[PDB]
Image (cartoon, rainbow over all chains, first blue to last red; front, side):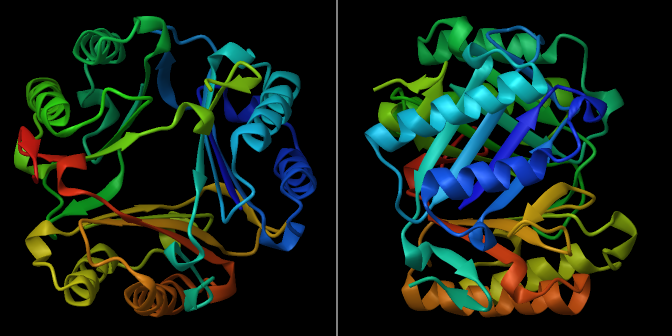
Length: 114
Length: 114
Length: 114
């Protein structure tokens, strides 16, 4: 799985250990081993949410399966919780796009996961 | 809606008010309330279009609905027009990927839109 | 076609000529003319792969067609090969998300490719 957070929160406001926490929590949430979790945090961005430059985040979670109605509600509660606690972003200023990737449409290690 | 523009135009060439202009125009074009429009501009990027490093932009628009052949033509004329007028990017050096997101695949406010 | 690579490798480790090499090799792999290939490299990123921060890459390839099981395996070999040779990223620390875009869902030059 791949989780990306783009945010206008400054780099200094991202706590040490945040990538590790995201890795651990996403491994537990998706049920996938942490070795297959990739995380990417992009602070200091020029962005707005609802016309406002108050703290916000635009995020994606790509996974081969483990994507669906109930799972995505649970991921959203988890990840909005982490962004509120660690980056002080309001949950109503977070979008998370979920992508259920076909194994044949994910490249890794000179081939695909198919 | 979530609109992202990645460009090699420098930050100083992005005019004041641009994120607000994008927010307003996307609200009107998509019909969505401005409170649901998120915009993200990423200048100073290392990118090429057709092998050339002349000004260019690589963009995405994700929306829950309001995506389709005629709508996307209209969005493209709007957004290429703004990028030409405001960032001096030629329309033929702009790509916009359109994504019709299922409500169950968008997280917001600790849940999803389903 | 549009190829994006996000990496923690520093900007100074991206060799001169890399965007041109990506453009050339993707034109040949996809069969599309180089005038239609866009490339974007984002170094110096805050990311982890499998819980660690040794060089890694998170990438996308969006293309109108020319996406499928065998083609994507070939793209993965080509692109992992380039990232290993040029950026010294291990192929097992690269993820590439492939997207087969409908022509009506790609904006360009004030309209779509439909």
